[PDB]
Amino acid sequence: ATIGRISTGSKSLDKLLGGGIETQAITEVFGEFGSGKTQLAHTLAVMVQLPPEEGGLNGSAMYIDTENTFRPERLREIAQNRGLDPDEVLDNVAYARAFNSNHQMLLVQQAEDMIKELLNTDRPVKLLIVDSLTSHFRSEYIGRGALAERQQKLAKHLADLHRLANLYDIAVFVTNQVQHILAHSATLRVYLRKGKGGKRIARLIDAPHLPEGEAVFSITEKGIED
Ligand SMILES: [Cl-]
């Protein structure tokens, strides 16, 4: 099945990504607090709703939050400043707080139910966001031997997410706070940091056959743009 691409709002970042965030893939964006990772998540939750000539997939989004970073009014702002109805856009973002890592796993199973329900409608789910994906795993699996167990549980969670992406042709977008020898299993990893002039800088990590470069973007009333 053809890979779909969701624009980030930034032409620079989209170029680095080969046109946008891919369906049938997990894209991980990681960095310090304020690096742009959560602003990008909010922006994508709007962009996915647009038609493809505007960089979207005519879809809806599901946003799983682990550290209370979801801001409904930020979504409404991004929508309004892109010519969209804020309330309709917010209603197309299904939100859930994950209370712990086991609940986070159940929420992914519930996401599958919603994806199946909407799959053949005019607005399928096309984006699943997990913000600060590792935060509960890091607090719960800690101490001697926790590295192996945590990594096994994370790998299983990521395998479940990969299955949804591949089976239902959706993009999975995950964020993490930055922590250098641990394994990772996202399809594509993107490091974000602050740069000069209020800009954020993006770099692909461990993607040897994707072209060499860095993207530059801003955080604005439209979410993310150049
Ligand atoms: Cl951010």
Image (cartoon, grey):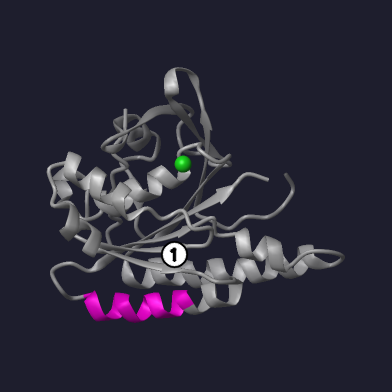
Question: Residue 38 appears at what percent x and percent y?
Answer: 44, 47
Residue that appears at 29% across and 80% down: 116
Q: Which residue is depicted at the point 34% across and 29% down?
A: 12
**Which quadrant holds residue 87?**
bottom left
Amino acid at circle 1:
Ile
> Where are the magenta residues, as a range?
107-119
Q: What is the chief secondary structure element of the magenta stretch?
A: helix
33 vs 52, left or right, is: right
- Quadrant in the picture for residue 117: bottom left
Disc 1: which residue: 64
- The outermost residue toward the top is 197
Viewer-nearest residue: 111 or 155: 111
Residue 54 to residue 110: above or below: above
Q: Is residue 81 above or below residue 131?
A: above
Which image quarter holds the C terminus?
A: top left
| Residue at 43% from the left image edge and 25% from the top image edge | 199
Residue 84 rendering spot, x and y as whole percentages: 14, 48
Position of residue 114 relative to residue 171, above or below, is: below
Q: Residues within 10 Å of mark 1 (few under 14, many from 20)?
A: many
Residue 206 point in image, percent of width and height:
58, 42
